[PDB]
Amino acid sequence: KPAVSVLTMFRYAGWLDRLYMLVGTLAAIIHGVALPLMMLIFGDMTDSFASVGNVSKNSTNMSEADKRAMFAKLEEEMTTYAYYYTGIGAGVLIVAYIQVSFWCLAAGRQIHKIRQKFFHAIMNQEIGWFDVHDVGELNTRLTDDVSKINEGIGDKIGMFFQAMATFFGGFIIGFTRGWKLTLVILAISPVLGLSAGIWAKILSSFTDKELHAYAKAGAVAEEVLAAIRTVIAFGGQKKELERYNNNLEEAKRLGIKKAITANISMGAAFLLIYASYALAFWYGTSLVISKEYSIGQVLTVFFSVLIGAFSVGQASPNIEAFANARGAAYEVFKIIDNKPSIDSFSKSGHKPDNIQGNLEFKNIHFSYPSRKEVQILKGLNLKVKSGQTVALVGNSGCGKSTTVQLMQRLYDPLDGMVSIDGQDIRTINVRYLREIIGVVSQEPVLFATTIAENIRYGREDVTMDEIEKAVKEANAYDFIMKLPHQFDTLVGERGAQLSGGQKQRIAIARALVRNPKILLLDEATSALDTESEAVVQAALDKAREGRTTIVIAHRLSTVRNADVIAGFDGGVIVEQGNHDELMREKGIYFKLVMTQVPPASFWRILKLNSTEWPYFVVGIFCAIINGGLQPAFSVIFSKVVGVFTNGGPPETQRQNSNLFSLLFLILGIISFITFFLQGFTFGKAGEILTKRLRYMVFKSMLRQDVSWFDDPKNTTGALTTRLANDAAQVKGATGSRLAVIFQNIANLGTGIIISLIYGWQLTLLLLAIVPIIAIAGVVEMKMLSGQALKDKKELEGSGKIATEAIENFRTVVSLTREQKFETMYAQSLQIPYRNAMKKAHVFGITFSFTQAMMYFSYAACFRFGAYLVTQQLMTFENVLLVFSAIVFGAMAVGQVSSFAPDYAKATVSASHIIRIIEKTPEIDSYSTQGLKPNMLEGNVQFSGVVFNYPTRPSIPVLQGLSLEVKKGQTLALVGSSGCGKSTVVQLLERFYDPMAGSVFLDGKEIKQLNVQWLRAQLGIVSQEPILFDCSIAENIAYGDNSRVVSYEEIVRAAKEANIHQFIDSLPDKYNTRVGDKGTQLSGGQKQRIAIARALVRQPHILLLDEATSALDTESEKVVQEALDKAREGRTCIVIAHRLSTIQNADLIVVIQNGKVKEHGTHQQLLAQKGIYFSMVS
C-alpha cells in the first residue's frame, strides 16, 4: 500500500503553517517533559519528609528543641515544593493550549486548500479518464480520504511529540538519577510484554474456534428459516427445534472452555505483573537498606521509567494515524499532479470569429479506452456544408454517438483530423469550442436549482427578459407559466417532476441562451411518445434555423426532411445522399424504412437469568473481594514507604520490607483465585443465558405463521442475525458488567472507608475535586461530539455540490460550467473554514483546562497534605494512603462510566427478544385446542372465499372462489398467471386466514379444527422441493413426525415414488447425504423424494403445486408416472401446467379474476370452446 513522501504532503502549508507546526511541536516537547519533572519534585518531597521523619522519632520523640527545627524546616520546604507544583500547572495552562491549537490550525488551513484543489483537479480530468475510473468511489474519496488526512496532520502530531518527549525525558530522569534500577525495569520489560503478548493471541485463537462452534447451529437455523414453508406444512417445528437445541450444547460447552481459559489467560499475566512489580520494589528496598539510594531516589526513577515505558503505548496509534494519512494522500495528490492532454481550465488555444460552420471529418479512427480490443471508427470521412443539417443513420450504437463526442472534442481521435472552417478543432481551446456547440442529449440532465438558473447555466450573465424570449422560442414557456412560482420553480430531484417533452425543451432553451453556431443532437426524438415529442420537434426546427447541425436521427420523419443523410455500417459510410437518392440505392437506409428508548426494562432482563441464583451469589461476592482488595494494594505500597519515613534501625528494615513484599503475594494468590472464581461463575452464567435465549426465540420463531415470514423486513438473513447478534450481546452486559460494577462499588466503597479512618481531612479535599475532574471528562466528550455534529452538517452542503457535479460530469463538461461548481464548492466551504479556525480554539481550551485542573489539584492535594503532617494529624504514609486509594478507586468508576453505554446496546437487543417471544401469532401451531375427528373421507369444499395477501393488500387475488372435491377424485386448478391457483393450496394448508368466505373439510370448518391434524392429512408436493442436509432415510421419514417409522415404511414409499432402484444402487444407499453438503441429485430425483415423503405420511388429501416445472422431458414423464400412482385412490388437488397431463383429471376449474368463470370435465370444457379450449390449442 503506497504513500507519499513527507515533504510532498505538507506542500500546501506555506510559511505561516510552518510557524504553527514548529511552535506547537516545541510546546509538545515542553508538555512531554513536564511529568518527568513532576516525579522529580515528588521524590524530593518524600526525602524531606523522610529526613525529618526518622530524626523526630529516633531521638527525643516529643520535645520542644526538636519540634521547632523540623516543622519550621517543612513549612519552608513544602512551600517551595508547592511553588513548583503550581508553576508546572500554570505553565502547562499556557503550553497545552498551544500544542493542539497550532497543530489543528495548521491542519485546518491546509485541508481547506486541499479540498478546493482536489475538486479543481477532478473537474480538470479527461472524460475518458472518467470511463476507466469508478465515479462512486471518487465522490466518496472527496469526503472520506480528506478526513483521513486531517486526522494525521491534526493534533495527533502534537500528541506524538508529547509522547516522545516523555519517552526520552522519562528515561533521562530515570538514568541521570538511578541508572541501576532502570536496568532492572528494562530487564523485566520483555517478560511483561511477552506475558500479555502470548495470551492476547491465544484469546483470539479460542475466539475463532468459538465462532466455528456456533456456525453449525446458525446453519441449522438458516436451513429451517429458508424452509419455513416446508417446516410448517409437515409439523417439524419440535423436531428442528431439538436439532437446534442439540447443536446449542456445543456452543455452550465450548463457551465454558472459552470462559475457563480466558480467566486463566487473564489471571496468569495479572500474576506476572504483580511478580515483576513486587520484585522492582523488593530490589528498590534492598538498595535503600544498602544505603546507595534514598526513599526518594527510588520513587523518582521507578515512576519516570514506567511513564516513559507507557509512552510508547500512547504513541503507536498516532504512528498508524500518520501512515494512514500518507496512504490516503497518495491517491489524492495523484489527481492534483495529473496534467491531462485535454486541459479544460486552459486559456491556451485559438479563438476564431465569424465561424460559418464548415465541418469536415477526415479519415477518423477511434477506440474507446475501456474496451480497446475493437475499433469504433475505421476511416470515417464526411463534410457538413455551412448552415445545412446532417442526419446520421445506421443501427443502434454503431458509431453515431461516437461522432458527436469527437465533435465536442470529448475524446482525442487516434488517426485522422477533425476541422471547423479548415482549422483543426484540436488547435483551439475546449471552452471556446464547446461554447459554440449546443449539445442536446437523448435524456436531459436538470439540476436541483430554479428554472431561471438551469437556463442561465448556459451563459450566467443573461437577463431574465432574454431568458423569457428563449423559453418562448424553445416552446416551453406556456408550460412553465402554468405553475405558481413559474420562473422560480425548482426542477429536479427535489421539486415537481417535468415530463420528457418539457425537460428537453428546457435543454433547448438553455442552448438558445448559449446561441451557438453549431448544434449537436443525439437521440433527441426518443425520450417519450409522439404526444410530447411533436411540440419539441417544432422547437428543434426553430433552434436549427440557419445553424450548421448534426442530428442523430431515430425517427423516420426527422430524417426525411434533412438536407443530407449519411448511412453508416461498421464505422464506414457506405452511402450518403438525399432521401430520394438513398431509396434508389436500396442499401441500409432503405432496409430500415421498410422493416420499421426500548420497552425492555431492567427487571425484565434480570427475570431471564433468575433461574441460576448461586452463580450470581459467588459472582457478587468475588467482585466485592477483588474490589475491596484494590485499596489494600495501596496499603502495602503506603507501608513500604512508611518504613523509610517513620524511622528505624537498618536491621529491622530487612524483616519489615520482606514482610510487606510477601504481603503483595499473599494478596496476589487471593486476587488470582478470586478473579478465576469471578469469571467462571459469570462466564457460565453468560453461556447458560446464550443457549437458553436462543432456544426460546427459535421456538417462538417456529410458532409464527407464514404471513410473518413473507414480510420484506423479516427476511431469512435478518432473522438469523437477530437470533445470533441480539442473543450474544446479552452475555456482554450481564456477566462482564456486573463483575466490573460490583468491583468499583467495592473499590470506591472500601477505598473511601480505608482513607477515611486514616484521616478525614484529606479525603474531603480529594472527594470534592474528583467529581469536578470527572465532570470535565464528560463535558469534553459532549462538546467534541456536539462540534462533530455541527461540522458534519455544514460539510454536507459542500459535498452536495460535489455529488451533483461528479455524477453529472458528462453534462457539465459540455456546458463549460466546471468553474461554476468549483466556485459553489468554495463558497459553501467558507462556513466550515471559519468554524475550523474556531475548532482549534475550542480544542486548545478544553485540553489545557483538563491538564490545568489535573496539576492544580495535585498542588492542592500536597499543599493541604503537607499541612496535615506538620500538625501531627497525619503521618506521611497516611497522606500517601489517602492519595493512592482514592485516585485508583475513582479511576475505576470514571473509566467504566465511559464504557458503561453498552447497556443501551443490550436493552434494545432484549426488547427484540422480548417482542418475539411474547408475540402470539394469528394461527397458533402449538395449540392443543381442536376438534380432531376420526373421519377419513377428505371431502374438500371452498365456499365463496375472498382473500388478499398480507404483503400487498391492494391487489385482489381471489374473489368468490367456490368448488367441491369429492372423495378420491382429482381436481385440477388452471388459469392465467397470478390468478390464485397456488393460493388455494396455501389456504387448505391454512397458511393464511381468509378475509371472507369459508373453507371446509368434510363439513367442518378448518378454523375450528386443530392446525396439526389438518396438515397431518395433507401431502404437500412443492414446486421446487427443499431438501435437508441429512440422509435419504431421514429426509423421507421427515413427513411422518413423532412416529417410530423405519426402513420398511421408507422402502415401500421409495418404490412407489420410483426412486428405490436409483437409491439401492447408490453408495451408502438410504444413508446417503443429499443437500448442499452431499452428492448433488438431479432435478428429477429431488422432486421424487418429496413425493416419497408424502407417501409415508399416507394422507387422504394430496396437494400438488406446479410440479414438473423442470426442463427435463424424460424425467417429467418418470415423475408423472410416479404422480399418477400416488393419486389413484386419494383425493387430489393438482396445480396443472402441462395440458396433456390434465386429460385424466376428474374436475377442472378455470379461474379468471379470482372467480370460477367455468368448470367441468376435460371433454366438456373443450366442447364449451371457451377459455380452456383456447389454452389447450
Image (spheres, helix red, strand yellow):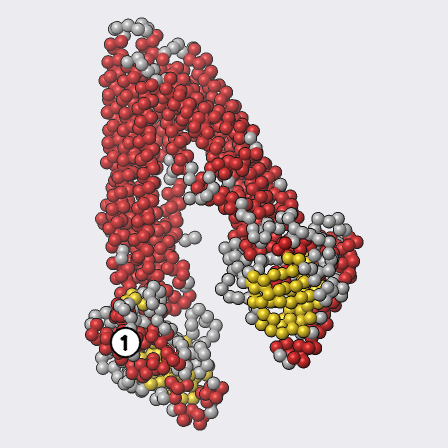
Q: Quadrant of residue 502?
A: bottom left
Q: Position of residue 909 (x, y in %)?
A: 49, 44
Q: Position of residue 665 (x, y in %)?
A: 49, 21
- Element carrying mark 1: helix
What crowding class fits label 1: few (fewer than 14 Cα within 10 Å), some (14-19), or many (20 or more)? many
State the residue at coordinates (50%, 20%): 666
Left or right position of 621 against 1012? left
> Where is the C terminus found, in terms of image quarters?
bottom right
Q: Is residue 147 above or below residue 47?
A: below
Instruction: Pick whichever, 1056 or 331, lies toward us.
Output: 1056
Left or right position of 1093 against 764? right
Q: Is residue 38 visible?
A: no
Q: Quadrant of residue 879?
A: top left
In the picture of the structure, the residue carrying the numbered disc 1 is 477
State the residue at coordinates (40%, 93%): 580
Instruction: Pick whichever, 436 or 441, lies toward us.
Output: 441
The amino acid type found where label 1 is placed reads Tyr
Q: Position of residue 785 (x, y in %)?
A: 34, 44
Left or right position of 890 against 612? left
Q: Quadrant of residue 283?
A: top left
